[PDB]
Amino acid sequence: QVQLQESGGGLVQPGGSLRLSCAASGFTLDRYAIGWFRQAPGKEREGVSCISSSTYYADSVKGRFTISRDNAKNTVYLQMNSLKPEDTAVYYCARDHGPCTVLADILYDYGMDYWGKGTQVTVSS
Amino acid sequence: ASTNKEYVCDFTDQLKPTESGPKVKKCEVKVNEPLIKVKIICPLKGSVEKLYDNIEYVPKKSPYVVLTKEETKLKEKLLSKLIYGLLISPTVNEKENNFKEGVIEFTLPPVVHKATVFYFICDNSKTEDDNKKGNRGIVEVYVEPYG
């Protein structure tokens, strides 16, 4: 019955904000690293951010996105400010038994499990 | 014409469940001369009771398949097409050359023209015992041009 549920997607204008939610059901997520990934349609999934039980940010979202974890709410959040059209994509969350692992500035995802169904993010003028 | 040098990465002890875990434990092999043999040792499930009961290996088909960077993705790729002429024996001390037997081995060729980096993971971070979590072992093989 383990589950990860993304929400918070929506449609905003450039410079707007959203907050994505990754809610754990049936386990406590503070024993796990939680990674945020995104996939524009037709393109390869890319790492966006990760929080372990430090933090990882893709260069393109540094200073605009903030990952955080609410232990009581059994949820990890991604606050996305100053959104740009390049940020449009389907955003996914997943859990890792290991630490946030970065190789050659890429978030390692082969340990990632229980991928949520994804939440759509669109930034358009 | 003959290999007389081998680099060995051996995680036999470092991936055991620990209270600080899971941690990344790294072994880097940097190669800049010809005909080097590389040997990677990782613990087996059941080698000790508990301790490795959920260990996993990435790529499962190592050493024939490796992790390597392609654009901004880490991809599983055939090693023999990344580096032409690499030698991989099907067996190692009469066992399959595969992490399910605890050891992988390969020998790099006489010439490499372009810097090439690839990785193997021996991942114990799903093994949990008594509040402790195993570690994620990463081997980075960094081959510089030579020959």
Image (cartoon, coloured by chain):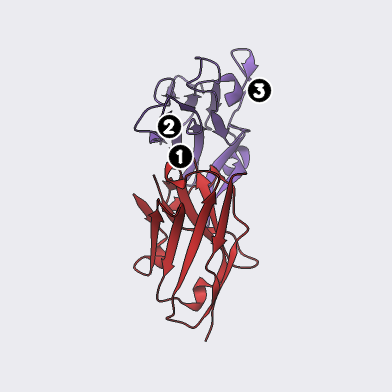
Chain colours: A red, B purple
**Residue, x 64% and y 68% (percent of image)?**
A41
Name the residue: 40% across, 54% down: A69
Q: What element carries label 1?
A: loop
Res A92 quadrant in image: bottom right
Residues packed near mark 1 inside 10 Å, few (<14), some (14 to 19) or many (20 plus): many
Q: Which chain carries label 3?
A: B
Q: Judge by depth and name the residue closer to the eye, B119 or A70.
A: A70
* Residue at disc 2, secondary structure: loop
Give the letter of the chain under mark 1.
A
Residue type, label 1: Gly
Residue at screen point 59% across, 13% down: B93
Residue A43 visible (yes or no): yes
Position of residue A36 measured from the top left corner of the image (x, y, whole percent)? 49, 57
Chain to which mark 2 belongs: B
Disc number at residue A98? 1
- As helix, strand or loop, the secondary structure at mark 3 comes to loop
Badge 2 amino acid: Asn
Q: Distance between the residues labelled 2 and 3?
A: 29 Å
Q: Which of marks 2 and 3 is nearer the N terminus?
A: 3
Q: Which residue lies furthest to the bottom in this view?
A: A125
Tell us which disc is closer to us: 2 or 3: 2
Q: Which of marks 3 and 1 is in front?
A: 1
Q: Mark 1 and mark 2 in contact? Answer it, CB < 8 Å.
A: yes
Residue A91: x and y in percent read: 55, 63
- Report which residue position mark 2 lands on: B135
Query: Hey, which quadrant is residue B65 in on the image?
Result: top right
Task: Report which residue position mark 3 lands on.
Answer: B90
Q: How crowded is mark 3: few (under 14 residues within 10 Å), some or many (20 or more)?
A: some
x, y percent for residue A125? 52, 87
Amino acid found under the numbered disc labelled 3: Pro
